[PDB]
Image (cartoon, rainbow, N blue to C red; front, side, top):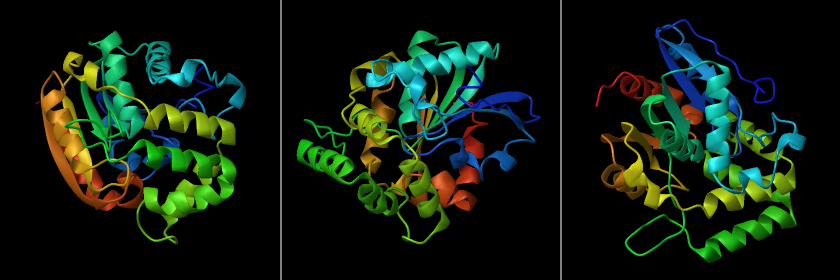
Length: 265
C-alpha cells in the first residue's frame, strides 16, 4: 500500500505526528494545519479507504463493516513506515479508530488527540449521543434517494457555517466524490457504531478536543470520554462552530491543537 492510501510524510520536526481525517473528507482537511506543524513535528498524512481520493476496488465492504478495519489499516500503514512511536491526531471517526488501534498496539501511541470524536451517536440510557434511530433512518433514506441532493443539505450543517463558505463547498465536493453506495455503507458503520465498552481498556493519554456547537457530537460526549477512558485524559472545548473546525476555523483551533500535541498529561 502507501500508494493506495496516498501516504505523505511532510515535515522536519523531532516528534512524529499522524493526521487522520474523518468521514466525507480526506487529508485535505489538514490543509491549514500542516504549515503550523512542519517546523516542530514530522507529520504523517494519509486517506482512509473509501474516500474519494481512493480506488473503490480496494474498499472491502466486509473489512470496513466495523471501525476495527480502519484501525488495522492504520497499524499497517505505521509498520510499512517502520514507526515505533508517534502522536495520533484523529478527526471525527478517526479519533475512535486510533483508540481501537491502541488496543492492538498500546505502545505505538504516546498520545491520542481526538477532534470531535464520539464512541456512539445513538442515544442510550444515561448517554446523550445526540441521535435516535428515527433520525438515523431518515438520513439513510435521503442518502440513497438523492445522494447529490443529500450532500447539498448535509454539508452546510456538518461544517456548520454559511452555505457559501469555502469549507462548506470544499467538504461538499469530497463528500460527493465518494462512490454513493460506499458512502451509504460507511455512514451506517459510523453512525451505528458502539465503542463505549472498550474505552476503559484504552490506556493511552487522550486529549479530547470538542467544538462548542457540533451537529454530530454533543459537548457532553467529550466529558463522557473523559470519565470512561482508562488512561489519562483532558477535555478542551474549542470556541468554534462546526464538525470540521481545523478546516472552517483554523486560526482559532491551531494554537489549541498545537498545545495538546505538546502536552505531557
